Length: 290
Length: 290
Ligand SMILES: Nc1ncnc2c1ncn2[C@@H]1O[C@H](COP(=O)(O)OP(=O)(O)O)[C@@H](O)[C@H]1O
Ligand SMILES: Nc1ncnc2c1ncn2[C@@H]1O[C@H](COP(=O)(O)OP(=O)(O)O)[C@@H](O)[C@H]1O
Ligand SMILES: CC(=O)c1cc(C(=O)NOCCO)c(Nc2ccc(I)cc2F)n1C
Ligand SMILES: CC(=O)c1cc(C(=O)NOCCO)c(Nc2ccc(I)cc2F)n1C
Ligand SMILES: [Mg+2]
Ligand SMILES: [Mg+2]
View 1 (cartoon, rainbow over the protein chains, first blue to last red):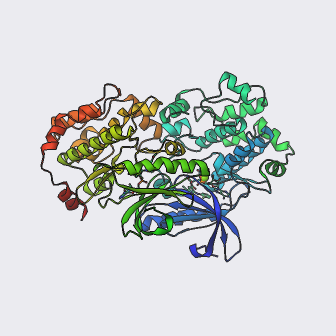
View 2: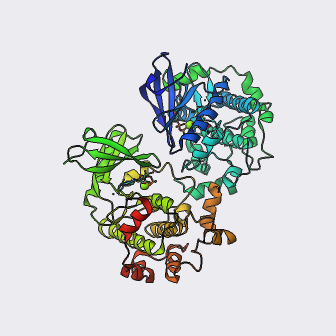
View 3: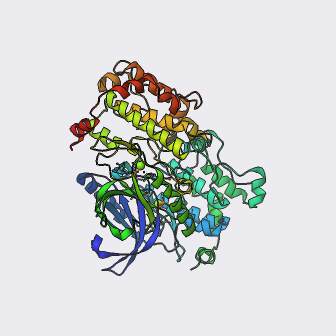
């Protein structure tokens, strides 16, 4: 059935980002609980219908590694995207309560991300464009899913006008120009894993003594770091050599030398995590409360 | 009297920016029309009261060059700032309808900005922090006023997390570090004048043949331009030498060599515009429709 504005009832607020709020809502006719994302945009009636028309491809996105989609519509200067509600939140929320995410678990996250990026590329011919912890959602039945990928050419456009002014997960090639594509997503995933592995955004890298301690930067300064300085590493010693090398392979500045989806899929760290009997479900509740 | 949420009625939307919507509203008990800015923030009950308490100094800001303030309060995860409604909008809106703002008029804008920055510094000991066309508001009775300056230390904090991802009006010293202060505002004003003088954001500078034509950039690319490349100039010929030199004085990369408020106040371009009988009121309506 068709989703429309009067059929919803607000339950609570799941969070906000740039120009978009996300509500936990009830779809009154179906009884279903959904997450409803609202994007406020000053756009003509014609292009909005393009946006909505381009958003319909989400109905064709069906993967255990991709957040479920219910439908998209336009309401009060708002574009609504209605998704499956992930009771576990995003991994940045999870990191905030957990402090640091264990390697074995990052192993599972990494598999879900690679499998999701692969799905989008193979079946839909698109890159993600916004891989970061907050766009990796998890739930109580143990599933790990990507959200907030760019399906709509026109929506990518009307949203060009702003980005997160502190942390960037953008690849050095994307920070410098047009010359980027899918390899860019590898960089963001790599950076996200380091953040989650370590307990904080990894640029600038942890101080010599700040390292065995665990175990405010300016806009240009930060970006100039990503572009011109050696990429972040996992600290030597407390992570397996295979993990260290996997993120090393992800964080290579040159996008052609950097590893791609098909090489990471057969990487030692994945082969290994793919074998492991890990109770992701049980871990997520033990750490957050479900 | 005290402003509160149920005493308001929405009239229309004046616009939006980062995390903040602005409504044209009616204050039902007084009958007054106001602009009401809402800032949505995930913040504890204690710091919010600090924010509100810090916002009260706006009651003490009374200058014909500073947008009027009615009051500030907290409502539904929203911080409300209620201001005088400026029926002329901001100068970016004005530029959009006008295409290009005449020199004589920029003369008046420049005087209003300098006089407003001076007021804030002399009487309140604060810098603006966000000088740009959209924070210069104008009205039908011909007044030119600054808005959106940082009065609240704590609010500056909870708002650190995002900035405009395309155009920056930030000074090179502010893009590179903590080492900035009031001189930074001079840079932004300078850049704003060039934009308004010329009809578009002046970085990168107009192409050789794109110049007598009038008469898509990446994040790092743009910032790297502001920091490492020569500052934008007005085109030679169609602006007075005095204007060209005034913005030159504003756009000096070194903040100590750059001109300050007291030097610009006695600059040839100001001395001259200060004499001129300019019908700003009449111009603003002739161009926008009042
Ligand atoms: N489908 C969902 N289920 C549960 N929580 C969600 C969902 N989508 C978004 N959220 C939460 O709402 C927050 C706001 O998301 P968004 O507007 O996409 O901002 P961000 O830039 O943080 O991704 C996200 O950080 C996430 O915590
Ligand atoms: N007091 C006001 N009177 C009339 N219009 C206003 C007022 N304040 C803001 N606006 C309009 O609302 C828009 C949204 O403003 P804001 O949230 O401060 O975003 P910006 O970053 O564009 O300044 C502004 O661009 C301006 O056009
Ligand atoms: C570009 C495009 O197609 C697009 C961009 C975004 C997005 O949510 N960006 O978030 C920024 C918040 O600050 C988006 N949303 C989106 C995409 C897939 C799914 I499953 C859920 C979603 F909400 N789309 C479908
Ligand atoms: C920091 C601080 O004190 C502060 C920051 C801002 C602000 O509006 N920023 O806008 C960003 C929108 O994207 C703000 N607002 C503000 C300040 C003065 C006046 I007169 C009206 C206002 F709405 N204050 C009072
Ligand atoms: Mg998101
Ligand atoms: Mg503003």
